[PDB]
Image (cartoon, rainbow over all chains, first blue to last red; front, side):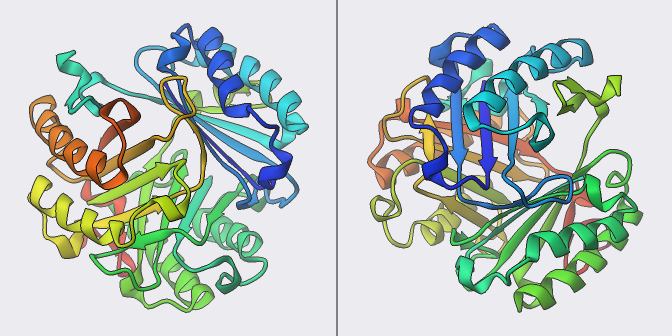
Length: 117
Length: 117
Length: 117
């Protein structure tokens, strides 16, 4: 899966190693192998969340098969909020998540697409 | 709604307070409460827009219900171009926007999804 | 088309002029005019790809009409991997691509949307 995290926390307020710990967390939450998890963290941005510029973070999660339903996204959301609130020292009011289903023809890897792998 | 703004203007050429003013602007344009508007600004990037590396900006707008039609996106585009050209001191040839409808099951907030709120 | 490239290579390890060369490359690969290609490069990020924090890059490609099939995305992927592996000095295991079809009502330009242009 593909995880992208935008935050207005400066880089030195994002704990060292977060991107690796987010791979492990996403593996357990989403039921995907940790070695297929991709994480991108973009710190030091200028952000407002819910109209406020206090420290905050935005997570996007894209995956085949597992982020397409309300019922399971509710579960994923609970677990990712637990992880991110503690890791980033942010309240639950300062994080939002978006979920994006992907199809195999959308994922380019090793010079082809997943449809053929 | 969720607004993301990429620009190759350095941070010191993006006027102070832009992310808050974009919340107010988006609230009026989209008919959503300002306290539900999220803005992410990513300055200092390396960008080409329409093949040219002159100063430029890319805006993405995601929301439930209001960014799904050509007719209303035409209106939203006009208003956001007015706002951004003046705020960023950019010509209309140096800005592009993309609109992305969202569904409630895609938005994670407070450890659940909007389907259940 | 719209190309976005995230990388954990620092800016000084992304070759000068890459965003312009990516416009030319995308024009030939996708069959679109180079003066309609948009490229955004976001370097110096914190990234894991396939669970590993070694140097890597993520490319997203969005366009009308041409990135919606497995068969042609397979071709696009091959060509973009050739370009990016050499430009960024990265192995094919360190790059992933995502393809996103767009419709004309989603693209805001010159204060309207492409539906009306």
